[PDB]
Amino acid sequence: ISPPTIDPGALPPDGPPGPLAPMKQNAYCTEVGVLPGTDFQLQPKYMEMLNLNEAWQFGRGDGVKVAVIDTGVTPHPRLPRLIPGGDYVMAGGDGLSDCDAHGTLVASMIAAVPANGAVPLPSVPRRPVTIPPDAFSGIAPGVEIISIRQSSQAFGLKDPYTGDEDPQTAQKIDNVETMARAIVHAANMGASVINISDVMCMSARNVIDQRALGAAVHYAAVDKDAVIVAAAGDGSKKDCKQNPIFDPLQPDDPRAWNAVTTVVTPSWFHDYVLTVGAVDANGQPLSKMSIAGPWVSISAPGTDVVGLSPRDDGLINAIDGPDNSLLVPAGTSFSAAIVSGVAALVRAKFPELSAYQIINRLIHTARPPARGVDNQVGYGVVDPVAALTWDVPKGPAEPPKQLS
Amino acid sequence: SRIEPTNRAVLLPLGLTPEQVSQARPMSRALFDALPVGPELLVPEVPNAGGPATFPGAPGPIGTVIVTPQISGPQQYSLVLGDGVQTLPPLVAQILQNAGSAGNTKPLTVEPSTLAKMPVVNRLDLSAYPDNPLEVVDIREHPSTCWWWERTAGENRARVRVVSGPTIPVAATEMNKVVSLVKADTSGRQADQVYFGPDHANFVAVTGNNPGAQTSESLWWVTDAGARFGVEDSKEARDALGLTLTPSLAPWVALRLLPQGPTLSRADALVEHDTLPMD
Amino acid sequence: SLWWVTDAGARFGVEDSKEARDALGLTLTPSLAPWVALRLLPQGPTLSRADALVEHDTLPMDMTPAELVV
């Protein structure tokens, strides 16, 4: 498959968020809970790799706007700087309630404020759910979060017929169009870090037309200077299947583009998007759970997740599964959250640098894998203190003239 | 820690001189990245300076320096904040007087009986400054400085220190067997010389640079000639090469400086060549 | 022109000078061969003392190799 190409004339016109056709809720919202025997007074195991106590000396990322394009967010007293951006699933929404449990976990992992004897906003005005002392803290407590509701599992079309196109593929084309719109809207809000944690897998056989999405990525990354960070895609999702790695018999292309079988989008645009893979809390790659595409560029932790509870006022560890079973979350959707926090702190300390330079600063300071550049992990594992203090060259990587 | 030659108020109490600072020697990019960053040596920023105090009997406006008479025992300096007073170390009181002088040269002397009535408060951080003058080393006699990292097997903490000397910390007899490397990479991220002393390690695992790191992220092999080669972490590669053993830890700041060769793996070696090129 | 052929089927050129000869050996007189046949074998670099005096940290990788099948 040939690498992506872009035609900037296809930008979608701006406008208020709203679905392409009327939708109705089909299922009840997901319940949540805590695994037996947890003690929230101990730090999460993933925070030991980041060494946050030393990274915070230069600041907590005050004055940075981060856009969370996902399943929305539910307000909580530990998130005092949340802004409602819009809704594309329901015409009457504003992105400020999540029925799938996914959105408040991702948002809280970035900006939840540490514990104190009293909360800044004791009021609790939040609405009910719709029907058809503590060691936890975010990576950058000073940021400002913008919420936009892009996707959900709980909603469906209320006139299901879709004509000459198969109802399975008919939904992918609606997602690609609705994703480009949210990226353009989020940039005009003035965000400086856009985080995308829900992504599409497609067969390499007759990929869907993405002209609108290509231009949308270029506009936000260059003309608005936003940093776009996206997940590599969890291998448990409906259509995601594993990609092949480097092949020693064909040194023609070291990232192996000719052997691709699954396409992940918008992650596909490696010239403007930073794609994050996953590793366990010890540093080994989660070889069985993340898609190893050729676009992958960096990696961060993805296990022992903790976060603020929707529908409650406390912490959580797991979400209620299909059965009575209580299911624990893990994967790239959370690793991309860690990098969104590190990216926010770095471009608070070096405000003169552009998006393309902030990305090079994170890439060059990461601990690399045995092959130097791989597909399960890109250049390596993220390193906060290193990104904030080493003297990185301003130009991109270049090979030596001669070795003898 | 960073310092500026224009700040005479801080240079003088520490024992530095504007000329001495301006004539300081260069620093390599390699060592610049290895040393951790500390807070800047600047005049303390006392908050809400000059306003009136909240508590009664305050000897002066907020931010003034107070001292107690020598006849009652060793003198203790202090600072008057908005809601109370906080103690000052001897060396910092001198910096505050010198910088906040505006023509004033001495603090207000107050007796214990009037001092004992003021409430004690703690509202500003001051642990950055040393408690006595700096013993600056004359670089002409010690032109060499190193960052040293070490970790003992079975320990949970690594030790970080700085060493200074007339020459690199190697035995005088072994100074002849330092290896001089070729240097294709001109970015200044590759060393000039490499030395393998006693109890060196061949098979290594990369770890974080801070002293509390516990991960073990990748395996490498370091040759006697100075180049490093990667090893794919698979049962077949480990057993074919004879590396079914536990590797020693190493930090990325030190290891990144050796040149990197091709990767060692069973798939990479199963290839035939007529003749090799020479770029 | 002087050439050396290996058992692996590759050919290498040898300098005519006393240094190159005396250093490798090859003092005996060579046999004659026709260029229309000898040119069919793959060629390697010439064995000149002037280019063997070089140092390297790592060598360049070989493009377009072939599979070794067991």
Image (spheres, helix red, strand yellow):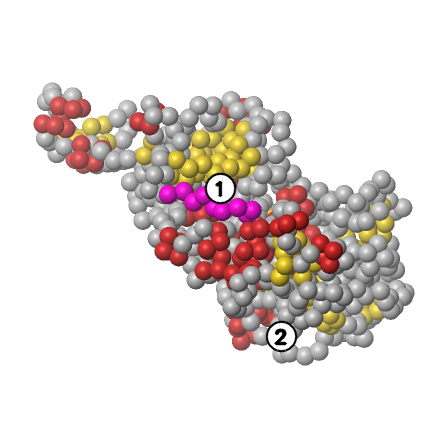
Is residue B276 left or right of A33 when viewed as pictured? left
Query: Would residue C60 be counted in the magenta stretch?
Result: no
Q: Which residues are magenta?
A: B129-138
Tag in front: 2 or 1: 1
Numbered-mark total: 2
**Chain ID of residue with mark 1:** B
- Whether residue A244 is visible here, answered yes or no, is no
The secondary structure making up most of the magenta span is loop
Badge 2 element: helix
> Residue A147: percent from the left, percent from the top?
72, 67
- Whether residue A401 is visible here, answered yes or no, is yes
Would you name the residue on which mark 2 appears? Answer: A188
> Residue A132: percent from the left, percent from the top?
90, 66
Would you name the residue on which mark 1 appears? Answer: B253
**Chain ID of residue with mark 2:** A
Q: Give, as a three-letter code, the residue at label 2.
A: Asn
